[PDB]
Image 1: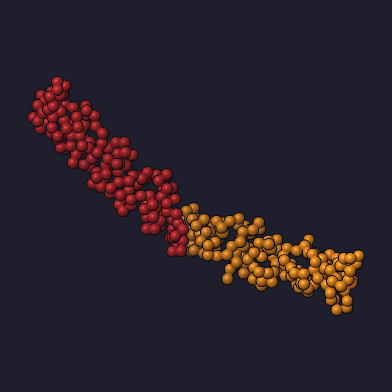
Image 2: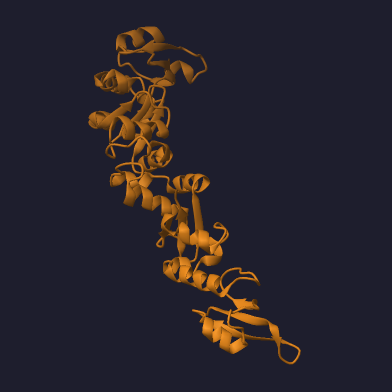
Length: 162
Length: 163
């Protein structure tokens, strides 16, 4: 699903739209042939894309392929929510650096669910009696967690960063 | 602080019944001598009083002294909060009978403080660990206790009546 639309700048500046959607890994000879570039692979720009991160018009094919490599080295669980993760981590460099400091709470839809997980099935505050359970303010604990950490809500659950 | 005005119903002086104020314990002989009752101590009634409870015109010296004994024997904090207790108990007699079923939470100002004590100090809901204590809804528990139990708020604390 990762793809970019690379246009010929020598034709676009004049008015004529000559480009194409390319998937990864982007091979230079294919681009050269498809949008009519020269031996130097000269004057192309990125005029549209479908990626989990921002890109400039003047971002090189080499930059793109490199980011694709880094994304591929990541575990599949992180790749499927990469866009959300790159909101906290501001770069793939950083995400990969701390990749193992991430916890995927798969069946949690909010901080209440995360609070109830740590208390009940983790024993984060020691064993809880039966009679006391209806008086534990999980909403309050989930709040104290969210304020004192980073929790990212997504379609594959809540991602917590240590 | 505690006294009653006892009138001789049969002895007048200057168009007004003979009477006097008496402090506790009300000495029978003193009364007889002061307001001039007969040898059988008859013909008297209580026409005024300064007591922390209600009492009738036809209440006997014996009953009064018995009420004084009962009040004096109560714990101090119950003594100073009689008016509040007698909105629950029907009489000093009944309060005295049930005095050992009254729990005096002297250190508690409201039901939160009472809930806090039962959970932390008593273990009424089992072992509450250190870190967990900071996230227990004590207002909720105190409200549940108040809705189903009997707790009276007073200036000398919360009194709880238990079966």
